[PDB]
Image (cartoon, rainbow over all chains, first blue to last red):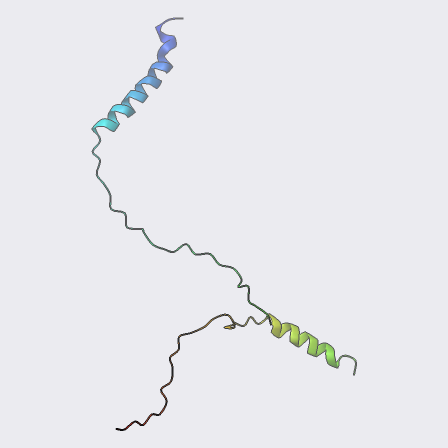
Length: 51
Length: 41
């Protein structure tokens, strides 16, 4: 049990830190939403009256 | 003379499968009609 047994955990922590500090410097820009539309209807059979 | 009505029943059932739209429940716009009117003074 030496400093070599901590290598995998060291890599786990290093990957977490790399992701975290690459998220900080990444530039973020808003995007335009162009998908709004009322196209989600439902079908079926009409309940026609009889008489 | 026994199968003369079997064909009728089969044709009635088959045409019953041809779906037909019904306006029985649907109404439409309308206007009052103007009646001939002569007025003088």
